[PDB]
Length: 141
Image (tube, rainbow, N blue to C red):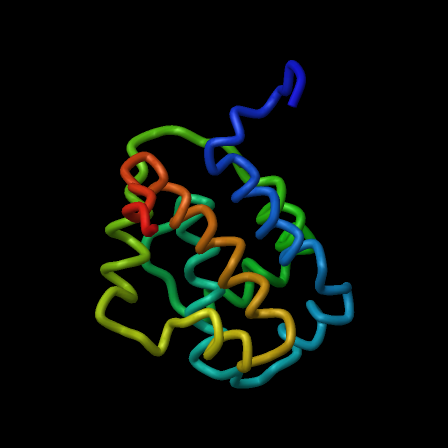
């Protein structure tokens, strides 16, 4: 590390997950959008994306029109990577899925090859707001 341009402090956490949204191919978008009635794991995933962009509550229908945009993935990956303005996503993603375990990297991942990677893109934007308090475990001889 010589004169790096990245603090590193859980900084690469928002770049790794991104690959998840950059992984899925175009055919993954048509399929996900072509789905008449996708699993719950999928619906919840799309909602999390809407909040990131700055959208409160929405329905699958309204979400469908949004994703229908060719900028669905482009905006998700281009979204304010290092945004800053009273991060309410914590209580948000929670109020929608706090005591709901059904929202787990796996469940969604199993939903449809493509959603999982998303559940991570967001998660990173979430679990990242913890490194500011995270405390490395105690030493163990």
